[PDB]
Image (cartoon, coloured by chain):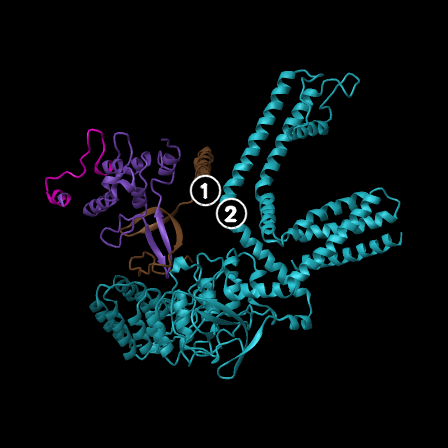
Amino acid sequence: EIVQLLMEHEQTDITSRDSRGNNILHALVTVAEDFKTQNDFVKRMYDMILLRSGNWELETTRNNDGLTPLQLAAKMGKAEILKYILSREIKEKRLRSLSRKFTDWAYGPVSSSLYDLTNVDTTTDNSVLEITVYNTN
Amino acid sequence: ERIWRLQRARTILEFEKMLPEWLRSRFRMGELCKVAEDDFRLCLRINEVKWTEWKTHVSFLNEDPGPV
Amino acid sequence: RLKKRIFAAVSEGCVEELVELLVELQELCRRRVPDFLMHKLTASDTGKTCLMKALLNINPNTKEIVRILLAFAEENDILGRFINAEYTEEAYEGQTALNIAIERRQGDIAALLIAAGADVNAHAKGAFFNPKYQHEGFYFGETPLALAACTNQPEIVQLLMEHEQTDITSRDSRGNNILHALVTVAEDFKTQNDFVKRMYDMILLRSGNWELETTRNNDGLTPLQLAAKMGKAEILKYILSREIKEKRLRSLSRKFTDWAYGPVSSSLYDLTNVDTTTDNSVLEITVYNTNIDNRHEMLTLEPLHTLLHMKWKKFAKHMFFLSFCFYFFYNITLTLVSYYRGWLQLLGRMFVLIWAMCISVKEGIAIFLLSDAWFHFVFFIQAVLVILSVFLYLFAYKEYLACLVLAMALGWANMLYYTRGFQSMGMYSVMIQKVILHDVLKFLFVYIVFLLGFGVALASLIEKCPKDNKDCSSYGSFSDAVLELFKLTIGLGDLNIQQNSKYPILFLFLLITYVILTFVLLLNMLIALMGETVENVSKESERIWRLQRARTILEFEKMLPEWLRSRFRMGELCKVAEDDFRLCLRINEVKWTEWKTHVSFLNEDPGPV
C-alpha cells in the first residue's frame, strides 16, 4: 500500500541510485536470500513495480560495480527471483513489451515458449551464463 | 550429477571462448524474432507440453501456428 | 487492400462495425462468382480464411463476430463451401474451424457451427496431424471427437455423439480409431490426473457394441494390443477390470461377479485375446515387448498374474526342473570325459552330441528371431565349442582339450541361469547380472589402463641389462611385469628392492602409487555399488526376476504343440447373458472394508457347482 502511495506521488524518484550505486531492484536482489525464509513476497513486489513503471530503464542500469540487477542476481545466489525474471509472460498488450517469455505457437497442450537471450548469449563483455558458471561462493 | 554438469558447463564455455568471433558468429544458437512495436531481439525457441491446466491462449504473436 | 484490412480487423477483433461496413463494401464489390468473393476473402497461400483467423485470434467480442460472419456467408449462400474449407499446407492439412475452436476450447461456437452445417467427420491428414518423433507435433487421432476426448471436454462429446451425422467408427490415415488415440495419449496418471479413463467409459456407455475394440489398426492391433505395445497401465487396469451393474450394457463388462455370500466373492475375468491363442496375445505381446519399463506394473494385475501362477502350478515347473536335470547330467558327463581324457562312454558321447545339437539349434532359431538375452549366445558358444572339440578329438590335434574345457566351465557358469528358478536365488542372480553389467566394467577398464601404464613404466626401468641371467631381471617381459602387478593386487606378489635397475626409489614409488590407486578405485566401485543397491537391489530384483520368469514360462509354453496345449489350457468356459459364451478364469478375493450388496450376479446358487 505504501509503495502504491509513493509511486502515486509525483515528487518520487524511481531511478534514484544509492551511494553504493545500486537501484531499487538491486536491493531486492540482494534481499531474497532464500524462498523458505521470506515466503516469496519479493517477486510480487518486483512484478508490481515493473507493472507500475513501463520502461526498460531500471533493468538497463549498472551499479558502481558495473552490473545489471540481473547480473547482480547472478553475482548473488538469487534463484526464484531469477526464474521470475527470465520466465516473464504478460497477457497485457500495453506492457507486453516487457515480458521476456513469449508464447507464439500453441495448438493445445503443446506450445512454443520463446525466451530472450539479450545479455545471456555471452556477447557483450559478460553474460549470466558466464558470470554464474565462473562464479564462486 | 550436479557438480558434473557444472564442470561440463564450465569446460563447454572454455572451448567456446577459445574460438574467434566469426566462427562463433556462425555457431550462434540465437535465432532472431520480431516482437510488437517494431521490437527486434534475439531468442531461443523451445517447445514444451502441459496436460494439467487448460488455459486458452489469447496472446500469441504468430497467427499461423506452425514451424513451416 | 481490403483482405489485409479484414485479417487485421479480425486479429485485433476490436470492432464488428468495421467489419459491418467492410462486409457492405465486399457485397458491393461482389457485383462480378461466389468463388470470386471466396478468393477475395481467402488467403491463397495456406487456404486459410478469416473465420480460421478469427477462431485463432481470440477475444471477448468473438461470438458476435462469428454470428456476423456466418449470417453474411448465409446471405451469400456460400455457407457450405466456406466452413468446410481446410488448409492446403502440408502440416496444416485438413484442420477446419471446428478443430481450431476446440484447440481454443470454445464449445458454444462449435454448437453454432454444427447448427450451421459443420463437418464433424472431417479428417486432419498432415505432418503436424500425423507426425513422428513425438516432438514438434501433436497426434490426437485426426478427428475432432478425439480432440475433445484428449482435451477433457465431455459436453462437446455428448453433443457430437448426439448428432446423427457423426461417424464414431471412423479410422484415421494411420489406421487408428478413437480408442487407439486415447491409448497413445495415456502417458501417466499423475500428469493427466486420470480423466481419460472417464472418457473411455463414457464413450463405451454411449456405444453399446464390441465393434471398436474388435478393430485393428494398419499395424493390425486392437487398442488393447496397442496399450500392450505402449506403456499404458492405468487405462489397462480399467480395460481388463470392467464391471457394469447396468443390465442393458452388462454384456460389455469383462469383470464379472457371479458368486458372493459376504466379503468373499468370485471376480470372474475374460481371456478372449489374452489366452495366447490367436496369433498374438496381451501376455505374449507385453512380455516380449521392449522399450517399456512399466512391464512390472502391467503384470501385477489380477488376471495375468493368476494366469502365470496357474500355468506354473499346472506344468511349467515340471518342465523347468526337467531341463535342469538333463543339463545337469549333460555337464556332469562332460566333466567325467574331461577328467578321464567302454560301451557306456560311446553312448554318453552320442547323447552329448545329440543334446548339443538340440540346444545349438534352439539358440540359433532364437538368435534368428532376435542385456536379458545374454544367456542364449553363451549356450550357443558352448555348444559350438563342444562340436569343435568333437571334431578336433577325431583329428590328430592338440587343441581339442582347450575348446572342450572352455565350454565345460562356461556351462558350469550357465548353471546360474537355472539358479534363477528359486525366489531368493532369483534375486541373487539378478544381482549378479546387474553388478557385472553396471558396476564392475568401469573398474576393470580403468584398472586395465592403469595396469598398462605402470607396467610399461616398470618394464622400462627394469630394462637394465639382466647380466646374462633371467632370474636377475624381474619384470623383464612386459607380460611378466603385468603378471607381477596383478599377483600383487591379489596379495601374492614379490615386493623387493629391485636389482638391475637405474632408479630403485622411483620403481618403489610408482609401485606403491599403483597399489594405492587400485585400492581407492576398488573403494569407489564399492561406493557406487552401495549407492545403486540401497534402492535398486530390492525393487529391481523382484520385478526383473518375475519378468524373466514370465519370459521363460512363455518360451516353454511356445515349445509345445496345440493338442497338449489344448489339454493344459487354464481357461474354463463360462456362460454369460444374451447367449454370450466366453472363456474365463475364476478368481476368489476378499474385501473387509466396503460393504456393498451384490445386486448383479450371474450364478443364483452361490457355490462352486
| Image colour assigned to chain A | purple
Residue C586 coordinates in the image, percent (x, y) = 53, 71
What is the three-letter code of the residue carrying label 2?
Answer: Asn
Distance in Å between CA atoms under marks 1 and 2: 42 Å
Q: Which residue occupies the foreground of this view, A58 or C193?
A: C193
Q: Which residues are magenta?
A: A3-26
Queried whether the magenta region covers residue A4, the answer comes back as yes
Q: Is residue C595 left or right of residue C438?
A: left
Q: Residue tagged by mark 2?
A: C536
Q: Is residue A126 above or below residue C178?
A: above
Chain letter tied to cyan: C
In the image, is residue C129 part of the stretch drawn in magenta?
no
Q: Quadrant of residue C104?
A: bottom left
Q: Position of residue C91 (x, y in %)?
A: 44, 63
For image coordinates 49% across by 84% down, the residue present is C578
Q: Which residue is mark 1?
A: B27
Which percent across, then down, holds residue C192?
39, 60
